[PDB]
Structures are given as structure tokens and as C-alpha cells.
Image (cartoon, rainbow over all chains, first blue to last red; front, side, top):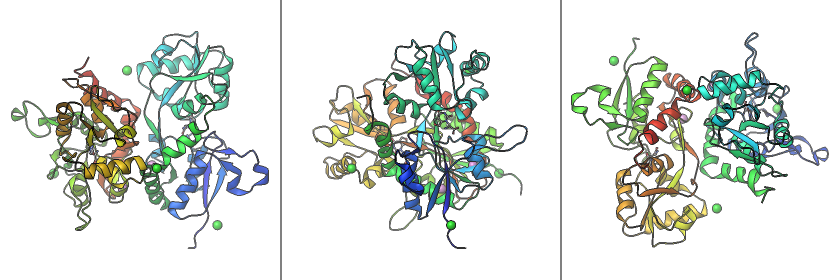
Length: 262
Length: 262
Ligand SMILES: N[C@@H](Cn1c(=O)[nH]c(=O)c2cocc21)C(=O)O
Ligand SMILES: N[C@@H](Cn1c(=O)[nH]c(=O)c2cocc21)C(=O)O
Ligand SMILES: [Cl-]
Ligand SMILES: [Cl-]
Ligand SMILES: [Cl-]
Ligand SMILES: [Cl-]
Ligand SMILES: [Li+]
Ligand SMILES: [Li+]
């Protein structure tokens, strides 16, 4: 039948998607800005569709409840037909790949350590061998799931520590994790995706840093419902944008051109 | 119908696939060793297929002749039905994605600069601004195609330099490029994939190094003919192996555990 406007699901997470300061004077997609807003515009331009940015209702990326078998988050919105495409910092994982389609990665990343400057930690092994410096992750998402599911000795030890540490080492949002690092006088380290770690390192008050190698090597992908015709074109668009250098340009724009730490 | 042995196409390129020193005393898949040999075994274990490693007849990765429209290399073997899967350091690119299926990446990489130690070059921009130190790429493959197709000023300038430089700055094999760096007294720099650059930096006589940031960010993928049923399972296997840390283990095994430079 006739073309329809493509429903995009995304999530408010700086610098990927933010409401503009003047959003009340704007309408529709123009209310938002960020890396994923720019990426959505480029994908739509190359694929020739009109689209509407919507914000995922439950604030989650995507996981399946073990009891009800229901998928939540942006993955769920795709699985249940509430959105046509997810354009967000959504990690390509096996369990998600089984239920939705993903483009090839538009950004590479790995789990990483954020410390307050001066914290005597250089690696995941360092954290795992001690408890004076508490450490944790988001309470939902692929970083938490990495530790929960790991059979690698160091990361399994870290997960056992995280589950049993008091007070809770988990946080609900990136902002909460960053604030906790900044306010804990070196006694909290935050495990988060390297992309986000790099972004925060260039934000005032310039008191955090990424330390150590990444713990894994993953990618973010554009997601569509399994079998959706849109998937092929969107994937070719990601590859084209990468080959043209435009994904690198967008990362530089949102991470470094605007950096606040010199 | 009944299960059939899966025909794998690959290419002799160290450390991905090499003939064992004692290969004459061995048969079948046991004649070969390397990262991609180990990876093929893990993929087959997880997917439950038997397979035969074969070596691509024409020694190429995969490109389409502009006049005849015929695909060569491992891509061609898939397109024309001569192999069922390609397991090799095969870069995911747009033009290839249009004709074959690719798994999500099993290895990340970018184009990079190899110098003989002491060469006064730190970046692609450095190379592009001069001619005393000649520089080039393989005469076939995705690294050459990156420069040929680039509309980025620095890389377009480098391509124009490479096409017009005398004597020819192109090489036919990785070994030829490495040898040329080693024998040219600092007057040749080799543009190659970062993975390979890192491998060579750990090989005697320990006289090369990787310099500068990568020029792009790409991945190697396992390839199957478009629409092949094997593609889904193989892709899930790559993701599982990545999530288990086994791809990192294989890279360490073939790059660093065996490193010859300390
Ligand atoms: N990418 C993850 C969600 N996520 C995460 O787990 N850790 C982080 O530090 C993140 C920053 O932005 C999004 C993030 C997923 O897809 O679940
Ligand atoms: N990955 C490339 C082929 N290739 C390449 O172009 N440059 C290199 O330095 C390589 C090392 O191994 C394979 C390589 C393709 O798929 O064409
Ligand atoms: Cl509509
Ligand atoms: Cl282990
Ligand atoms: Cl057979
Ligand atoms: Cl440019
Ligand atoms: Li999928
Ligand atoms: Li494809």
C-alpha cells in the first residue's frame, strides 16, 4: 500500500538524544538533538522515508523477563510492532539478535572503567582484587548482563562482588553513575560503555577519566523487527555512511568538537 | 535432503590460515593452522556441521569487474555457488553486502600505517604532505578500494599520489609490503589493516611499527551466499563466541602469546 511514516523508537541519553533547550518552541523531530538524531536524519535521507522520533515508553534498551517471556525496552517495541526502527546506543547481543534484526555496527565500543581522577585503579583485575573502592553498573542493560552472564573468572568474581556489596553498587541512569563517581571521593568506580566514558571525560568539571583496556568488544546497531523490509536498506545506509566518514564526523561533533576539558 | 559437508573458502594469509610445517604428513583440514582455522572449528562446533577447508582459486578477497560484472575472489565463490561459507579476514563493505550475507564482525580493524622504525611519519596527513617517503597499498582488496573511492581530502590526495608515484607503490601480497618496508631504509611506508600491522609488529626482526590512528573503522565478517540458511546460525555463533571471550582468546593466541618481540 501507500508509504507510511516510519516510527522510530529511541531513548533520552546524552549525547545520543537530548531535548533541545528551546524544545517548547519547536515541534516534532526538531525538539531533539544529538548523535542519534543526526544519524536518523542521514539514514532517512539515504533510504527515502519520512519518520517520527518517539521515546521508548519504559526507558529500557531490551531484555526478556525470564518468567513472562515478555521483551521490554526498545527491543520490545520492535518485537510487538509498536515501532518500526530503533536508532539508539543499542548493543548488538546474541539474545537480542535472535528476536530482532540489526544493522552492522554504526559505533564500536566495549565495557570500560570510569574513575574519579586519582583513584588507584588501572584495570578490571585491580578492581576485582579489592573492596575499598566500590564498583558497579547500571541496573539494566547490556553492561549489567555482561557481568551476570560471564564465565570469565575476573568478571564472574566482579559480578559476585557487585551482587553482595553494600550499599548497592548499582545505579539507574548514566547520570547517577557519573554523579556517584564524582561525589564519592575516589571510592566508587563506574563500569560503563567506553563511548559514554569518553564523552563524560570531555564534560565539566573534567574530574573523571577512562582507565584500562576495554573488557569486551561490541557494537551498536540499528534495529528493526525480524524480517522487516526496511532492514536491508537501513543496513546499506549504515555501511555507506561509515564508508563516507560521516559516522566518524558525527562522533567528533558530539564528543570532541564540543569538548569542555581542553 | 541429507546433510552435506559445508565447503569453506579461505585464503592463505598469516596468521589467519597457514599450511602447517608438517602438512605433508596430515590430511584434510588438519593441514592448516591459524586464527581462521580455529574460528572455523568453533563455528562448526556451535552450528553442528562438518566442513572442508578449501583455498580460493584466484587468491582474491572479492571485487566486481566494472566491465564484465563478474565477482572474483571469495565473494565470487559464494556468489556463484562454488563455496558455502567464507571464513577469512574479509572486510564487510557496502558493495559486498549487496551481493552476499555477512555475520556481525568477528574482528574490528581499520586501515593503518606501517613504518620501519625511525621513519619520521606519525599520521596519514604527514604522508599526504610529502613524497620522499613513498607509500602504498595492496594492488587488490578493501584497503586499495578505500583510497580509490574516498572523497575525503587527505585520502583522495593520497590516492592521486599513489596512482602517479614512480616506481609503483603497490604490492601484490602482505609479505611483499612488509619486506618492502623492511628493505627500503625508511623510504617506504605500507598502508594495511591494523590487525595485520599489529601482528607484524610482533614478528622478528622487530623492525616495524604501527603509527597514527586508524584511518577508518571496519570489521571482518563471515560470509555466506545471499539468503543461505546457514547465515543465521553462523551469525549467532559469532556473537556467542564473542560474548564468551573466545574471539579475544584467539587473537591473543595468534598475535601476542606467540609474539617474538618481547
Ligand atoms: N548499550 C546498552 C545500554 N547501555 C549500557 O548498558 N551501558 C552504558 O554505559 C550505556 C550508555 O548508553 C547506553 C548504555 C544496551 O544496549 O543495553
Ligand atoms: N580484508 C581485505 C584484504 N586485506 C586488505 O585489503 N589489506 C590488508 O592489509 C589485509 C590483511 O589481510 C587481508 C587484508 C579485504 O577483505 O579485501
Ligand atoms: Cl502515516
Ligand atoms: Cl577465565
Ligand atoms: Cl558431502
Ligand atoms: Cl574532507
Ligand atoms: Li537478529
Ligand atoms: Li549482504
